[PDB]
Image (cartoon, coloured by chain):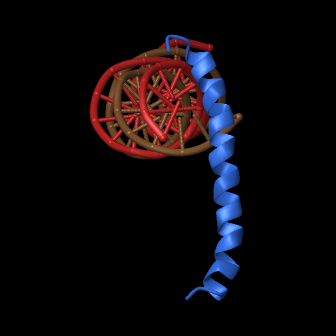
Chain colours: A blue, B brown, C red
DNA sequence: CCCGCTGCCGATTCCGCTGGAACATT
DNA sequence: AATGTTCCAGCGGAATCGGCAGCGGG
Protein backbone atom coordinates (compact mmCIF):
# COMPACT_ATOMS: atom_id res chain seq x y z
CA UNK A 1 0.00 0.00 0.00
CA UNK A 2 1.75 3.13 -1.28
CA UNK A 3 -1.16 5.43 -0.36
CA UNK A 4 -0.83 6.53 3.26
CA UNK A 5 -4.28 8.14 3.24
CA UNK A 6 -6.13 5.10 1.91
CA UNK A 7 -4.38 2.87 4.46
CA UNK A 8 -5.28 5.42 7.12
CA UNK A 9 -8.98 5.36 6.16
CA UNK A 10 -8.99 1.56 6.06
CA UNK A 11 -7.60 1.62 9.58
CA UNK A 12 -10.11 4.33 10.46
CA UNK A 13 -12.78 1.69 9.86
CA UNK A 14 -10.56 -0.93 11.50
CA UNK A 15 -9.75 1.09 14.61
CA UNK A 16 -13.33 2.12 15.16
CA UNK A 17 -14.05 -1.62 14.93
CA UNK A 18 -11.57 -2.43 17.71
CA UNK A 19 -12.91 0.51 19.73
CA UNK A 20 -16.46 -0.86 19.50
CA UNK A 21 -15.14 -4.34 20.30
CA UNK A 22 -13.32 -3.03 23.38
CA UNK A 23 -16.37 -1.14 24.63
CA UNK A 24 -18.70 -4.11 24.14
CA UNK A 25 -16.27 -6.57 25.76
CA UNK A 26 -15.83 -4.21 28.72
CA UNK A 27 -19.61 -4.07 29.07
CA UNK A 28 -19.91 -7.86 28.74
CA UNK A 29 -17.18 -8.57 31.30
CA UNK A 30 -19.49 -7.60 34.18
CA UNK A 31 -22.09 -10.35 33.84
CA UNK A 32 -19.51 -12.66 32.23
CA UNK A 33 -17.63 -12.61 35.54
CA UNK A 34 -20.91 -12.59 37.48
CA UNK A 35 -22.08 -15.93 36.04
CA UNK A 36 -18.73 -17.57 35.22
CA UNK A 37 -17.89 -21.12 36.30
C1' DC B 1 -9.65 7.74 12.96
C1' DC B 2 -6.49 5.78 16.14
C1' DC B 3 -1.88 4.91 18.51
C1' DG B 4 2.87 5.62 19.29
C1' DC B 5 7.23 7.12 19.25
C1' DT B 6 11.11 10.49 18.16
C1' DG B 7 13.04 14.19 16.15
C1' DC B 8 13.47 19.01 17.18
C1' DC B 9 12.19 23.46 18.13
C1' DG B 10 10.49 26.48 20.72
C1' DA B 11 10.62 28.88 25.33
C1' DT B 12 12.60 29.39 30.02
C1' DT B 13 16.34 30.39 33.15
C1' DC B 14 20.49 32.15 33.96
C1' DC B 15 23.75 35.25 33.08
C1' DG B 16 26.02 39.47 31.08
C1' DC B 17 26.43 43.63 28.58
C1' DT B 18 24.64 47.89 26.83
C1' DG B 19 21.87 51.72 26.75
C1' DG B 20 19.14 55.14 28.59
C1' DA B 21 17.49 57.75 32.33
C1' DA B 22 18.24 59.64 36.97
C1' DC B 23 21.14 61.10 40.31
C1' DA B 24 24.36 64.07 43.06
C1' DT B 25 28.14 67.13 43.04
C1' DT B 26 31.64 72.49 42.18
C1' DA C 1 25.63 73.46 34.45
C1' DA C 2 29.37 69.30 33.18
C1' DT C 3 30.18 64.99 34.59
C1' DG C 4 30.66 60.73 36.81
C1' DT C 5 28.16 57.30 39.19
C1' DT C 6 24.24 54.63 40.08
C1' DC C 7 20.15 52.48 38.53
C1' DC C 8 16.92 50.52 35.61
C1' DA C 9 15.64 48.27 31.34
C1' DG C 10 16.35 45.47 27.42
C1' DC C 11 18.77 42.04 24.29
C1' DG C 12 21.30 37.85 23.51
C1' DG C 13 24.12 33.52 24.39
C1' DA C 14 23.76 28.98 26.19
C1' DA C 15 21.92 25.17 28.23
C1' DT C 16 17.80 22.49 29.18
C1' DC C 17 13.81 20.39 28.26
C1' DG C 18 9.25 19.51 27.24
C1' DG C 19 5.69 18.97 23.85
C1' DC C 20 4.29 19.97 19.19
C1' DA C 21 4.08 18.01 14.71
C1' DG C 22 4.52 14.69 11.49
C1' DC C 23 5.27 10.04 10.50
C1' DG C 24 4.68 5.05 10.46
C1' DG C 25 1.93 0.87 12.44
C1' DG C 26 -2.29 -0.96 14.40
Q: Residue at x 64, y 57 (%)?
A: A22
Asked where in the image residue B24 lies, by quadrant, the reply is top right
Front-most of residues A14 and B8:
A14
Q: Nearer the viewer, residue A13 or C8?
A: A13
Q: Is residue A19 above or below residue A12?
A: below
Between residue A33 and residue A12, name the one nearer to us: A33
| Placement of the C terminus of chain A among the 4 image quadrants | bottom right
Image coords of residue A26 (percent x, y)? 66, 67
Residue A13, position as x, y percentages in the image: 68, 34
Q: Is residue C13 left or right of residue A25?
A: left
What residue do we see at 50% from left, 15% from top? Answer: A1
- Return the x and y of residue B18 as percentages of the image width and height: 43, 16
Give the side of residue A23 with respect to residue A11, left or right.
Answer: right
Residue C23 drawn above or below residue B26 = above
Instruction: Out of B18 and B6, give the one closest to the viewer.
Output: B6
Task: Kindly indicate the quadrant of the structure image that contains residue C22.
Answer: top right
Q: Quadrant of residue B4?
A: top left
Residue reaching furthest to the front:
A37
Residue at screen point 63% across, 40% down: A15
Image coords of residue C16 (percent x, y):
33, 42
Residue at image point 71% right, 69% down: A27
Number of numbered labels in the structure image? 0
Amino acid sequence: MRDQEKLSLMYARKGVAEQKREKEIKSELKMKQDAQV
